[PDB]
Amino acid sequence: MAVNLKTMMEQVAQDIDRLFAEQLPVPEDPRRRLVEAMRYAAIGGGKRLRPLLVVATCALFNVDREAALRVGMAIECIHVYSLIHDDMPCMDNDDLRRGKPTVHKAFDDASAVLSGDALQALAFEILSEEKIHTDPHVRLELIQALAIASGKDGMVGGQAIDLAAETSTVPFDLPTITRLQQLKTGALFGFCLEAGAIMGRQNKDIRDRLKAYARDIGLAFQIADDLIDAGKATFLSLLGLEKARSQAQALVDQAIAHLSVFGSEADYLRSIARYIVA
Amino acid sequence: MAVNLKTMMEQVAQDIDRLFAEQLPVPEDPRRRLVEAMRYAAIGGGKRLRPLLVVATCALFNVDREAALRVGMAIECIHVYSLIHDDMPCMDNDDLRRGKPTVHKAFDDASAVLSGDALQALAFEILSEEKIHTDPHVRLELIQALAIASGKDGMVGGQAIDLAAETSTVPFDLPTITRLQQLKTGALFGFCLEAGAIMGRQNKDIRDRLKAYARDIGLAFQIADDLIDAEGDGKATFLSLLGLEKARSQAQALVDQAIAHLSVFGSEADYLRSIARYIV
Ligand SMILES: [Ca+2]
């Protein structure tokens, strides 16, 4: 099961890379720097957790594979742009990323701002195209979901809470850092899973179960990260080492449990929760 | 015509303020600052030129007025976020915009980055809702058009060309600054006019006439801007390249050209006609 996953992963990574290169031809005009920055940030980089989730979820319902990949690129556009902006000096001020210089270092601050801005627009351009799905109602569902997942009630909202924690001398509580995770990383994860239910025209019960999986692995992910990282409150600082470890493991079990109404079609999502999140 | 135009402008301004206020409730969780930054930028502008164009174009056909206004809010999301990101120290460093301190000044740099980021997302959320149009294809057409108009092949692409001009010692030529305008400001104007055609379920011939109007007023607007800014005093501009007399006459000709695209409409197009003349 870990081998079928490790190879799904590689197929996904090379496909997303292909899609981005194809989506981002370098224009023969002064937009050259902008698009080269977009390609620099979007191509080659991450392990494509988000496109992977989209592909693995769409596989529950035998969704058109190609369209599933493009939805993957759309969510990855949002993820990548968020990283470009997060890395900037006024934010996390990071010099490196994938062992490679961040956009504002390789290019400049303004190029980082604009390349991120363009990638957000591109996510919606991609989702909007007819190749995604013939049912227009479907495409609208994906677009509304992504817009909510990306903005003030989603990823950016989470970024903002994180910024508030860093600039406040009042330590946050467990409910607030939980809400922080739900928005900062959980919104995009939730989109990945929900996109599958949408692409498959599934019912509320199935939609709810997939979003619960996303909810639970997202939290497990952050708890694990709060452990790996070792002044603001964290799951480690609030739960302590022992309970944080046990709660991360419990969340993984829970995430898998949400998929229990599925047969073996849900096996990729099971593996993702273990051999990646755990 | 200018009298009704002023009235429409004041009305659109009030409506857009109402709509943004309703769209942006302030949470008591730590997202408070983000949303207050969004409200600060979006509310109490602001001539709302882009909402005005949407409203005046939808008026050509039988489009629900509140729906037209919401599309106006959506395009204004893109415009406002673009100003927030443009004012930042990384870009133009403006501490002020029409007597109003910029977001990074009233708040901080990080809040300006995020409030702009959230506003771009908000534009697409707004367009996706059924409130806009019962027909799903109308909404999808608007969304596709906005994403193209906003990104690397639109507004941000234009922003990039401008940034390239400012950080190079090689003066751009007429073709390049023409492309610069088409993208930097022309793309959003194009959306405003095309949105009216889309909301009105209009044919390709009508859509093209409207986009041609946007193209012409957008160029005229930039030429007039190149003129205005010069009156109040080294990258190439329409003024530097064309010279004073040619830039003046071309701005004027472009207004006439913009209006001529509307010759197939009756008095319902008077707002758009006035707006074009106003852009001078
Ligand atoms: Ca600028």
Image (spheres, coloured by chain):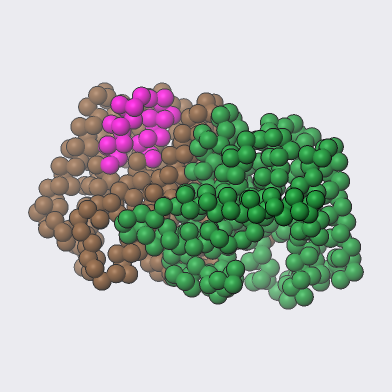
Chain colours: A green, B brown
Residue occupying the point 34% across, 30% down: B207
Quadrant of the image for the N terminus of chain B? top left
Q: Residue furthest left?
A: B245
- Residue visible at 42% across and 24% down in the picture: B201
Q: Is residue A173 magenta?
A: no
Regarding residue A188, the answer to whether it shows in the image is no
Q: Nearer the viewer, residue B29 or B185?
A: B185
Residue placed most toward the observer, B250 or B94? B250
Res. A249 image quadrant: bottom right
Quadrant of residue B279 in the image? Answer: top left
Q: Which residues are magenta?
A: B191-215
Q: Nearer the viewer, residue B171 or A6?
A: A6
- Magenta stretch mostly in which secondary structure? helix
In this rendering, the answer to whether A102 lies above or below A131 is below
Q: Position of residue B33 (x, y in %)?
A: 60, 61
Above or below A131: residue B186 = below
Relative horizontal placement of residue A24, taking residue A14 as reference (left or right): left
Residue B162 lies in quadrant: bottom left
